[PDB]
Amino acid sequence: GSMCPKDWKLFGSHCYLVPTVFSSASWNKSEENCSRMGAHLVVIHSQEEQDFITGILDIHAAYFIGLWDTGHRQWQWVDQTPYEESVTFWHNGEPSSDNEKCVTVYYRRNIGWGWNDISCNLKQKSVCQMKKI
Amino acid sequence: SMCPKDWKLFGSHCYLVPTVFSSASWNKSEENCSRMGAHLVVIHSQEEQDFITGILDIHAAYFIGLWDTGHRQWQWVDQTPYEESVTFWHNGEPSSDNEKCVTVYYRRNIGWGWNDISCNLKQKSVCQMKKI
Ligand SMILES: O=P([O-])([O-])O[C@@H]1[C@H](O[C@H]2O[C@H](CO)[C@@H](O)[C@H](O)[C@@H]2O)[C@H](O)[C@@H](O)[C@H](O)[C@H]1O[C@H]1O[C@H](CO)[C@@H](O)[C@H](O)[C@@H]1O
Ligand SMILES: O=P([O-])([O-])O[C@H]1[C@H](O)[C@@H](O)[C@H](O)[C@@H](O)[C@H]1O[C@H]1O[C@H](CO)[C@@H](O)[C@H](O)[C@@H]1O
Ligand SMILES: [Ca+2]
Ligand SMILES: [Ca+2]
């Protein structure tokens, strides 16, 4: 049958969903909602994944991704796969603050999509991924 | 056939050195295997180590499905248990806390063994899947 659950979007080996009804939540609560679906906050390893994920988002909203600071700019993916500084999509001037331990993706007008470090406790939208069948 | 076209049978698994896909990072290599319904090789025996290395070029290094999730906390990409007593590290390996991804390569007059290297370095790779 289908490689993805109903209403999930296929790209590469993964299935993606923006949980629309789940209202804005903290990074921990967003990861927990992904987890309830057998998924994780998105783990963005490539330009192709950054482009696909941002293609299914609303340019007017900011979305938590599965990247967090375990120390002092020691970025870790929620699935613990390697973080590669050379393949990142930080907005200009980001990351900005050792007090901002979670990461969102949002659209800057006349620039495009990029990552921003933010307070883990701020409520944001999110995007989930899982392996396909 | 137990295995897809161009894949090689050993035990309950099919193995492939990807060709259309040139040298790549550990993450890109793992995604390339996953797109084929496969994963980077997970090595649970001497026989698997020998079969996998048997189908490689002694002049190249190949990513395997082993990486450090923290501080010498080695994990297989299929979540099967890491057993330090059934490993094939080269002498002096794993060498460095900043080398988080594992390659298998040939040392002249020694043979094949594992080396921790930087995850960002481009290497060849080997994929594994269950047979049909
Ligand atoms: O504009 P707000 O109030 O949302 O946030 C303030 C600005 O930072 C934001 O924008 C920059 C990009 O210009 C990002 O790097 C940053 O992550 C924020 O999204 C100001 O530029 C910044 O100097 C200021 O500190 C920041 O305040 C917010 O963040 C603080 C730390 O999380 C909170 O204590 C504060 O209440 C507020 O939420
Ligand atoms: O430039 P290289 O020789 O290919 O790699 C070196 C590496 O950058 C440096 O940090 C090491 O001190 C040096 O020995 C080289 O390391 C390679 O070889 C050792 C084994 O001899 C491996 O353990 C390393 O993972 C590198 O492959
Ligand atoms: Ca910031
Ligand atoms: Ca090494």
Image: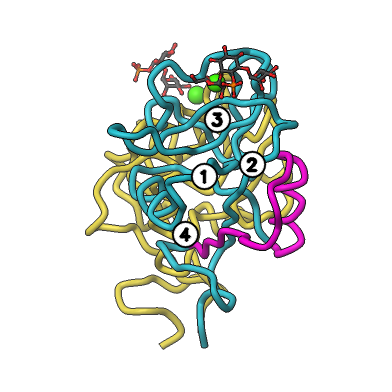
Chain colours: A cyan, B yellow
> Of circles 1 and 3, which is in front?
1
Distance from the alpha carbon under mark 3 to that under mark 2? 32 Å
Q: Amino acid at mark 1?
A: Ala
- Label 4's element? helix
Mark 4 or 3 closer to N-term? 4
Instruction: Single out the mark in the foreground, 4 or 1.
Output: 1
Q: Chain of mark 1?
A: A
Label 3 packing within 10 angstroms: few (<14), some (14-19), many (20+) = many
Residue B2 magenta-highlighted: no
Name above or below for residue B20 compared with residue A84. Answer: below
The label number, if any, that marks residue B100 in the structure image: 3
Looking at the rendering, the stretch of residues picked out in magenta corresponds to A14-38
Mark 1, Cα crowd under 10 Å, few <14 / some 14-19 / many 20+, is few
**Circle 1: element type:** loop
Asked whether A57 or B67 is in front, the reply is: A57
Q: Which residue is mark 4?
A: B51
**Type of the residue with mark 2:** Gln
